[PDB]
Image 1 (cartoon, rainbow, N blue to C red):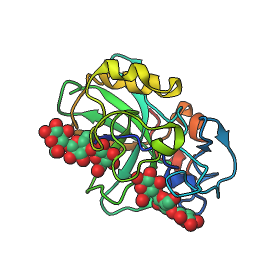
Image 2: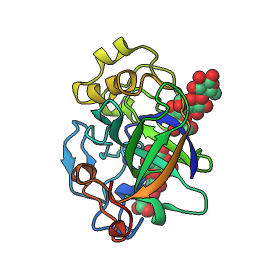
Image 3: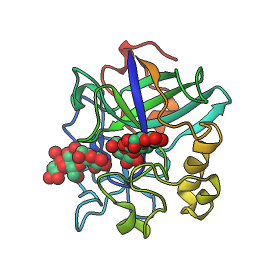
Image 4: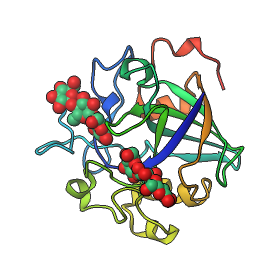
Length: 210
Ligand SMILES: OC[C@H]1O[C@@H](O[C@H]2[C@H](O)[C@@H](O)[C@H](O[C@H]3[C@H](O)[C@@H](O)[C@H](O)O[C@@H]3CO)O[C@@H]2CO)[C@H](O)[C@@H](O)[C@@H]1O
Ligand SMILES: OC[C@H]1O[C@@H](O[C@H]2[C@H](O)[C@@H](O)[C@H](O[C@H]3[C@H](O)[C@@H](O)[C@H](O)O[C@@H]3CO)O[C@@H]2CO)[C@H](O)[C@@H](O)[C@@H]1O
């Protein structure tokens, strides 16, 4: 199918981080304010007052080679819902921008009220907090515009160390692509992605392996 992308990092607990969202073995892991994995899936999101659960820093993209990367995204898929997309993995083939022709496999770990139809909001530290700002409470805040985040690669140099790799990826593998278009199909989640979130759908084994 065809989709549109944006970029984000708001530090909030991901929506597929709650139990009862989808038919999975366990929800996506959340972390404490110091980027360390916690196991209380009922823990209050850090984007809410008195919350303690934030997005883990390892739920960020990385390059496997110059034409292939792995990562995560907040999704809104037409005709579906959180029960259908939480923890599902999708292979995106970019169709526009400087990354046209490259592919990336992402695991869907959340969604947003502002997402349109077939809209993938890629997890990218420095890509913009958007509606909620959980990074201020978590560690003091991230630089950049509310929507769109930072604009230069050297601005990644002052990020908390755990968020640096994801920040640099944006300018390195991704070439600072500005909301590139893509084609997508559902795939079985690579073991590398489930190792970071802990979350695998019961129906994962029905889709093609990458
Ligand atoms: O039902 C479980 C718990 O839900 C809590 O609300 C969360 C929503 O379930 C979840 O959809 C939403 O997700 C946010 C996400 O954190 C944010 O990063 C993204 O930009 O937007 C999403 C959609 O708004 O988070 C909320 C808040 O944590 C209830 O608060 C809780 O009582 C309930 O048990
Ligand atoms: O709301 C969804 C997510 O949006 C992310 O910001 C995007 C803006 O929503 C999107 O409108 C903006 O698009 C720009 C584009 O980058 C710019 O070059 C063009 O000239 O103008 C467009 C319209 O303003 O792009 C950003 C970045 O993807 C938020 O960063 C994210 O938190 C939020 O969930």
